[PDB]
Image (cartoon, coloured by chain):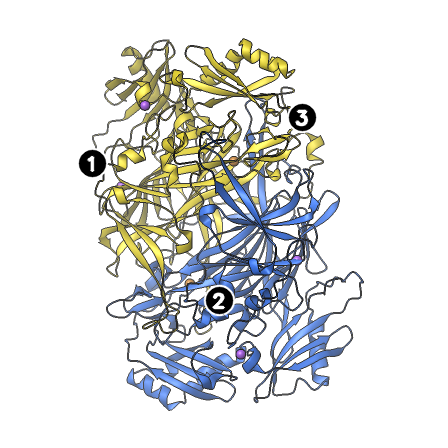
Chain colours: A yellow, B blue
Amino acid sequence: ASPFRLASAGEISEVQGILRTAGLLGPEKRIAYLGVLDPARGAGSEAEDRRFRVFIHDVSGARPQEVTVSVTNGTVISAVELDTAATGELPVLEEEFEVVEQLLATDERWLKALAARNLDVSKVRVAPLSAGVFEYAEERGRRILRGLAFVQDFPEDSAWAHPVDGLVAYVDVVSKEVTRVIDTGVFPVPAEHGNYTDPELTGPLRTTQKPISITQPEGPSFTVTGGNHIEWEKWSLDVGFDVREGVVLHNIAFRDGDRLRPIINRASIAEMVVPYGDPSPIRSWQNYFDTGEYLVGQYANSLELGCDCLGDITYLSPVISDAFGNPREIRNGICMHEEDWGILAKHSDLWSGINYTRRNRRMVISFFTTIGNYDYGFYWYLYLDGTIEFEAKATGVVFTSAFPEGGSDNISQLAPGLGAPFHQHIFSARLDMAIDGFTNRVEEEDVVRQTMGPGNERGNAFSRKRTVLTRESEAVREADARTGRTWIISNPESKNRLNEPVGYKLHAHNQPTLLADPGSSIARRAAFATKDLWVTRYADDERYPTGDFVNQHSGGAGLPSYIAQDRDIDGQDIVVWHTFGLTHFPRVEDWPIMPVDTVGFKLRPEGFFDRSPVLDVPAN
Amino acid sequence: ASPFRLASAGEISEVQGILRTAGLLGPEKRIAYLGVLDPARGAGSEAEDRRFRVFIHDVSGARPQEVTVSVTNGTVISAVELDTAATGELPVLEEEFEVVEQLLATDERWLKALAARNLDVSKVRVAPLSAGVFEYAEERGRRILRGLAFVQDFPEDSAWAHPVDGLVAYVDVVSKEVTRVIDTGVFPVPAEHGNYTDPELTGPLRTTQKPISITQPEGPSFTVTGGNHIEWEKWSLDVGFDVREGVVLHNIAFRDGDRLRPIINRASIAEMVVPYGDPSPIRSWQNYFDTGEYLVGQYANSLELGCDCLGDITYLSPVISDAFGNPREIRNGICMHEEDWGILAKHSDLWSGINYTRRNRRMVISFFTTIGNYDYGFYWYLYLDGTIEFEAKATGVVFTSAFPEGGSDNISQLAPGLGAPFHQHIFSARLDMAIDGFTNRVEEEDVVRQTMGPGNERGNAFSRKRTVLTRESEAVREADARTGRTWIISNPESKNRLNEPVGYKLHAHNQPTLLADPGSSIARRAAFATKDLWVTRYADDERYPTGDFVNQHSGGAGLPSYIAQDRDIDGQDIVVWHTFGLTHFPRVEDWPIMPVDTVGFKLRPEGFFDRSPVLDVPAN
Ligand SMILES: [Cu+2]
Ligand SMILES: [Cu+2]
Ligand code: NA
Ligand code: NA
Ligand code: NA
Ligand code: NA
């Protein structure tokens, strides 16, 4: 009955039938995106209307369409034709990936390049990558993928160990034309294999690891109702899944005595960009928008019990649409479990004689996605003490190149002749805030140093200052780790028992933001990534920091255009957008498969409660 | 047989007997510090000599002594009389704590102050705190403690809820004289209790938490030999314990194929300072050097199975000396166990068809200490992939004051009339490095942004730069989070298979350093805390960043004086000193007992291995 329930296979089948009967899903059409729309603000009328947003591609060259459908009423609400040279191309289709390798295999220029290098075309894998927007005028309004080549010596070989540098091709995947083949010179193909299951590389496996058994004899402490509604240790939330964003958290709230207190209305990772820092023309165009261009949810892994998720695991299996509108289940795509998290609070008091220890735990909601060579885990954590944390886990195989003789300022050497270009992995968290309700404001908090003098005669004092962000034009903020800068989201109309506004504090990791020149194509298309924090006024259509159609969009969409409205954000319905990321200079230890590295952020209560919220935790 | 073995009760009894027979341990003497000395450099002659360093206090006013004893040979090696006005006072003795409250109870000025506030002297607890060095000329060369008062309504009451503000006393604990009683005015004593086990405050305890059972059916994967030698998943180390520093890690090494490769010779937390930022004269002198003044090891907790340490736990019970030289066991003072740590590496490859997942684990070595109101956990972690991490966990009860009517720039309000002064918790990690041996160097690594132009026509390139620190005068470094600054410790004489020097990278949390005015007493006495990173040339006598005798030392001892030697550190035996800490603006949620907050650092391999060191981890 909940409007936030996961899409069902029956809903997706009805969307398919509605589109087909309306004449919108002929044999030349493909669904590039399908997802449920959230309830609009003011859904307190119970008049549920389950609506789906659909992007429809046409493989014959006709204009694509954006369509909204009401499953409840069985009708098409709107259908608009898209001019993609203006507003951007649709996301990349899984079926277009294989088109690239097949088309290049019959192109005389590609074959000539492979022949010069003595490579068998049957052994050459092509990584099909998004194109971006650069100097090529013929690409405007066409769907282009660019291809980089890797050699697979045998069917189980890791092709990533054998990059074919000096060679790139561009392909129009609708007209099935190879537009350009660029060959800048022959590099030796690195010869060492990278097969991390080969006993010749691993050596004998360790026999020293003894089992760690994690069980819950009475079952888990959380409950799941309505398919996706979670209650756990005073937390309440709904777990959504969207094919673009992946796991989305709705209606995060905390039961404080008799009141269910809202904290976050919607939390998601709304974009993620992987820009490469190698100036070689073979790779200087290379930027992945994993969320906006590829859709991270559709590549979610099925997670294996005991390997991917350890303990007493509860799975969700979300349903998405395939390119023809058939429902497809991602079996065991979302893991949920609780974890012991060490000591929560401890004190041994000499005067009272009381010794007190309590243990902490966290609730984990996670999924994993695989896009080509990289694998990313997305982890949301809820803690007993009111802390909310997100963590991204990056692993997989690093993207490779030749290592030039004489070295490089922009590429690490991993093995003889084998390089790995420098790059970043940058995320945007979209936090539709609802601290005790929707009237919220953001303050920037800096530590303040004080000079020795009158009123500070011993020179020990220090303080802090808070600056309210009042309008969108002043709400684009940078980190300052040296001044301990944090941001507080508070509700000026809701006070704790000390008559102070209730709030939550955002703690960033203060990692570098986008490093590219501000005049670059990627800085224009990923402007969100150039600043640590943005605050906007909520609006239904302002969903992604990069806009709706990221693929081959010329730039400026999303956050820079939203904030030009300069709206009031002082005690209003607001959205916080936090940029955070990893700057990756690959190390030898990252090869041939990379150990996990992590980045994230957290929010902690700041006078939200009237005292510690975990006094009622039992001794265990 | 190992020279790094823990001190035994028999060794400490022999030290006592050697001191007593030499005439150094009469009835007026107290042992303020006793610890084993590490082997000097070049102990490859097997000629073991177990030596102990002892600080001896005299309760009659005679000069204290520093004494070195050889248990092996049963002799006093040296005994030097100390001039404490010059080189500092000895650490505070546990038995001096109770002297303060008892002496004030019979002082007419103290009694007059308590009478004006209608407080029963029998209910007034006095926190005995270290004195520092300020404007009081009569304190030079005397052992002073300062006392702040709290009301205990009944024997099990938390006195911290009832600070008596406006009142402080100074006490000479040797002559048993109250030197000064300062009363700046009557503040109301906050009346709400802070008893976190009182059902009236906790409410009914939760019944919702189901058990999490963590067991190891075949026992743990590590072995313990010689009392304190650990082998675990290719790691090898010795776990030491010192009454001043607490847990010390020796001889950290990694078994890479057939070679035992050293990484860190000695790792410890060599100082920790808690400076308060309230300019009130009642508290503006307040700075704890928990390690150097109080000795954190002697207040280590006995850790309870299932509450403090969960899982298959192996305990060490270190032995220390009491003030008379009797051995005292800290039962179950050190926990050791391994923990599952999520996904180690994962990739699902489309081209090869191979799906691969491996799990991570870490080895945990931890202890907890309690000094007055604060409790601190010290955690060392070793990971499968070669990462070494330290984490400090801060909990306990915050130090309180009155909350002034009309507010404060330097104090948080926690409850009606109850304040908590701003403060920091700053740690110094001393890392005696031995990356593949003792010829090491430190490089500072910054991200380098590049401008769009020739050779970077698309403006996407970025790079990094490394600066070698060649002499001590240039090796005092500051964090720069915005440029991704890290430090690499490498061995220029040991190369990986790519002919690059092997190294480890230090990743800091980039939290603010000491905030006090640089002209303050605390900035002079805790100069280490004003900078993020120091590198010195190893020397036997350069043990602590604050010097040997921190209590009431006028300033400048330790790191600022060491680095004035300006020694060569480019490919030499070096020591890295890393400052890191928490800046604490107390929140309502910290009251009446504080949930854990954490800070730390980590070191990750950087071309130390020839490829990932965890390829031989089995599928589990
Ligand atoms: Cu990477
Ligand atoms: Cu604190
Ligand atoms: Na355009
Ligand atoms: Na909002
Ligand atoms: Na002095
Ligand atoms: Na060293």
Q: Is residue B173 above or below residue B614?
A: below
For label 2, the residue is B273
- Coordinates of residue B477 in the picture (x, y in percent): 52, 56
What's the chain of the residue with tag 1? A
- Coordinates of residue B72 in the picture (x, y in percent): 77, 72
> As shown in the figure, which amino acid type bears the numbered disc 2?
Val
Q: Is residue B249 above or below residue A591?
A: below
Label 1 secondary element: loop
Q: Is residue B226 left or right of residue A464?
A: right
Label 3 secondary element: loop
- The mark that comes first in sequence, 1 or 3, is 1
Do the residues under discs 1 and 3 have CB atoms within 8 angstroms? no
What's the chain of the residue with tag 3? A
- Coordinates of residue A390 in the picture (x, y in percent): 42, 43
Quadrant of ligand 4 in image? top left
The residue located at (57%, 44%) in the rendering is: A213
- Coordinates of residue A508 in the picture (x, y in percent): 41, 47
- Residue A42 is labelled as 1
For label 3, the residue is A191
